[PDB]
Amino acid sequence: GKLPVPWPTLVTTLVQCFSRYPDHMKRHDFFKSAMPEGYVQERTISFKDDGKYKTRAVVKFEGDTLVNRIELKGTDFKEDGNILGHKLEYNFNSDNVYITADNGIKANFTVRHNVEDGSVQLADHYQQNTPIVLLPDNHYLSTQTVLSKDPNEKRDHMVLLEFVTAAGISQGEELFTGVVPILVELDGDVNGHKFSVRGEGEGDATIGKLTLKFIS
């Protein structure tokens, strides 16, 4: 009927090729350099004092559409914890995603999810991307996200708006010169509860903008 986990816990899993890289940093944009063939993005997301997600995503162009197709496996979540207990607030904080080269890339960052009781649930992210390219110097992605709802959507859903810019110190980049349609498909299992998510929207790497609507 609906998602077995809170929507905010899925936000990071549900396309960093849409980050805006400053022109002073274009030599360091792995994600676009891998297009159109794309990259595999794999994470381990450790929810401290709770379970973890292991994800594997294929991110690539299929014709004119940037596709993000995901398998997610969630294990060891506590029935009464913040996640399966649905105690997370429906919002998101800013993050810095720290990137370094993998001689692809690796990235690390810790998401802070706000709990109903003012406390904080940490989601520690370990990330690796391998091409299906530009190996970058150390840098990070400054990420901003807002979560909302569609007034006339009847299905369990999440509207997401995101802005991402690289900071802190190759022909594929040409595929991102305009607004690019996005398709996201997630096949999930958390503690044995199988679920799927489908999302559509568009990305505009000129401004680093993402706008998507996901339904479960």
Image (cartoon, rainbow, N blue to C red):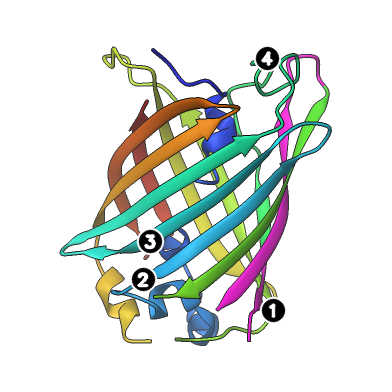
C-alpha span from label 2 to label 3: 5 Å
Q: Are marks 2 and 1 in contact (CB under 8 Å)?
A: no
Which segment did they paint magenta? 98-118
In the visual, does 10 lie left or right of 71?
right
Image quadrant assignment for residue 139: bottom right
Point 60% across, 36% down: residue: 74
71 up-or-down from 127: above or below: above
Secondary-structure class at tag 3:
strand
Residue 138, numbered label: 1
Instruction: Provide the residue designation for mark 3.
Output: 59
Image quadrant assignment for residue 104: bottom right
Magenta stretch: includes residue 110:
yes
Of callouts 2 and 4, which one flags the residue occurring earlier in the amino acid sequence?
2
Q: Are marks 2 and 3 in contact (CB under 8 Å)?
A: yes
Q: Are marks 3 and 4 in contact (CB under 8 Å)?
A: no
- Image position, residue 69 (x, y; %): 36, 51
128 up-or-down from 156: above or below: below
C-alpha span from label 1 to label 3: 22 Å
Specify few, some or many for label 4: CA neighbours under 10 Å numbering under 14, 14-19, or 20 or more.
some
C-alpha span from label 3 to label 4: 31 Å
C-alpha span from label 2 to label 4: 36 Å
